[PDB]
Amino acid sequence: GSSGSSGTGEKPYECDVCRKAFSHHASLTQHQRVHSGEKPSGPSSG
Ligand SMILES: [Zn+2]
Image: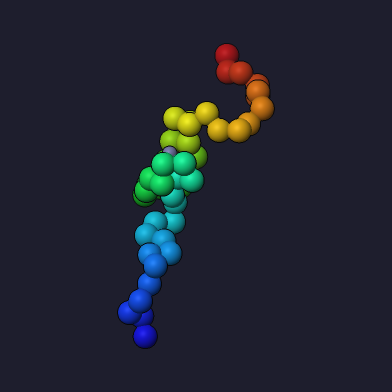
C-alpha cells in the first residue's frame, strides 16, 4: 500500500529555482519574476 513515498510532490505548483510552493497557478508564473531566468528580451511594457 501507500507507505513509502519520496514526497514526489506536495503541491501542483513548485518553483524550479527556489523550490517554493503556491496555492494558485498564476502565483507561480508571477513569482518566477524574482528570478532572472534564461530568456531573451521581450516587448517592454509602457
Ligand atoms: Zn522561486
